[PDB]
Image: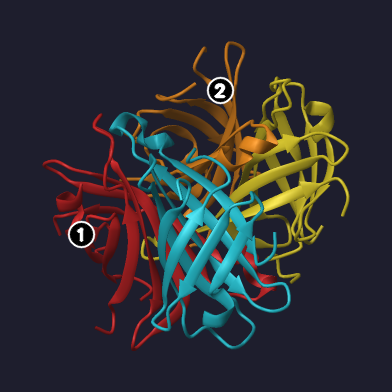
Chain colours: A orange, B yellow, C cyan, D red
Amino acid sequence: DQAGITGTWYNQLGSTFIVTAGADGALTGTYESAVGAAESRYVLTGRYDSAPATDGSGTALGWTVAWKNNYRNAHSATTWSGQYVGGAEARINTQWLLTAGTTEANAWKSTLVGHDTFTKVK
Amino acid sequence: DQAGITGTWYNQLGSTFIVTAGADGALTGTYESAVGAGADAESRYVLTGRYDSAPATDGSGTALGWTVAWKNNYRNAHSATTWSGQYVGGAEARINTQWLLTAGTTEANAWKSTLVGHDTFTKVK
Amino acid sequence: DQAGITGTWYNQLGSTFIVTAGADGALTGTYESAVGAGAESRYVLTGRYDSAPATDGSGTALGWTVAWKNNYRNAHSATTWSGQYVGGAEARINTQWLLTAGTTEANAWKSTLVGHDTFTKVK
Amino acid sequence: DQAGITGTWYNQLGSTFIVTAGADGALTGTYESAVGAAESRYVLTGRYDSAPATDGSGTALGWTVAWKNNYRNAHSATTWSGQYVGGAEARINTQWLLTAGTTEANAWKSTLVGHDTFTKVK
């Protein structure tokens, strides 16, 4: 939910994700990757279920980073798709797709798939 | 490209994606799914995303992604899809994507939370 | 679906998949990729399929693996295709695939490509 | 490695994977899922890189389970794609695709994606 999601998250790679959850279901913030790629911060936008189920289910959400800022351009974008799980050890459990710009001939090897787990602690 | 991406796109399922590409790399718009929204404004959902606003010029595609949370003022599927892919320009422009759709689940069902697919968007139905 | 699956398939890249489906649910054969991986370009495949699918019009679930090592080449990687066989006049195998390359722990985050191949019985 | 892979492996769900790696790069064995499931055991076949890199890289591998045996049929197949990393705390790190049989109308929601981590310790 909104209060649970807003703030700073860290994944298993040491990347930092800072996000504000809007009451309208918006996600806005900045992503700092510990791997690949002000110089190493990138805009992110996304959406989340602002009215989740109240049976203990997680909160569905996703966001995108385009790996271009004012300094740098990796001609790629990542989307994270997952769910926020609240409680003392709150997590965002994600699967991600990273697509690099390619010619048609190389499109078959355009997309990386992975999983990040974000916690509020390092 | 910004000029190439802005507009109305249709996928192989018959879903409609309307997007504005900002000079800053923002994607904003609405998504109407032909499937899974109780139909086989009702079926319209906010989307937001990002794209490479300075793509390569060698005929490489333009990397982008966007998200839809499947909640509007009518319905809630307690789920979110993210599309990751590339825009390819030309007479027959395409956005080729792979998508992940995560449903809210208990920790028990988390292993079966996430669908994976692929959508191809064109400017004609 | 055993009769349907057994034979030679081609995907949108021009790759060739020859497979025998066993009555036990085994898939065995050889894969030739038109892309990457440089008989020099044939690789062993093994997999499984549902040998008693639903009769209700649903496809037949199946998957197979190729390790990209033969007697001539080694790309230090393996692809798995997960999908369903759809029968009839224009029979198809609709797949999604994961390709993992061997990596150091440092580079594991970029170890895995994901894609989709459609196989038809004609080029 | 052949000796490194061969044996019994356990994932974070508590599923059990027993596998023999052949000298020819073959993987053969049985899989028991703790979730969704002799009754609860299923044939698996796969391949692995039998001459991996000598640079500290993991060993690429994959395998399939069709969720039919003598007792049960979930009309689906899972493929695991990943790598074996040897040493004191040996792991098989995978991502997986589970396709269910569907009608053409429901093909869009045919395939689940996940990640399992296998260790030799229960």
Measured from the top left, where is residue B43 in percent x and y?
Answer: 77, 60
- Residue D58: horizontal and vertical position, in percent? 28, 40
Q: What element does badge 2 sit on? A: strand
In this view of the protein, which residue sits in the foreground, D120 or C120?
Answer: C120
Query: For this view, does A45 lie left or right of residue B38?
Result: left
**In the image, residue C44 above or below residue C61:** above
Residue drawn at 77 percent across, 42 percent down: B94
Q: Is residue B66 above or below residue C2?
A: above
Viewport quadrant of the C terminus of chain C: bottom right
Residue D100 in sight from this viewpoint? yes
Q: How many marks can you see?
A: 2
The answer, for residue A49, to whether it is visible in the render is no
Q: Which residue is mark 1?
A: D9
- Tell me if mark 2 has few (under 14), some (14-19) or many (20+) residues whose alpha carbon lies within 10 angstroms of its own: some
Q: Position of residue D66 (x, y in %)?
A: 41, 73
Along the line of sight, the residue nearer the viewer: A30 or D57? D57
Report the mark closest to the observer, 2 or 1: 1
Disc 2 from disc 1: Cα separation: 39 Å
Q: Residues within 10 Å of mark 1 (few under 14, many from 20)?
A: many
**Quarter that holds the N terminus of chain C:** bottom right
* Residue C63 drawn above or below residue B1: below
Q: Label 2 marks which chain's residue?
A: A
Q: Is residue D71 above or below residue C78?
A: below
Q: Is residue C101 rendered to the left or right of residue A112?
A: left
Task: Give residue A42's mark.
Answer: 2
* Chain containing mark 1: D
What type is the residue that disc 1 sits on? Trp
The residue lying at 21 percent from left, 62 percent from top is D20
Residue A38 position in % (x across, y down): 52, 12
> As shown in the figure, which amino acid type bears the numbered disc 2?
Tyr
The answer to whether tags 2 and 1 share a subunit is: no
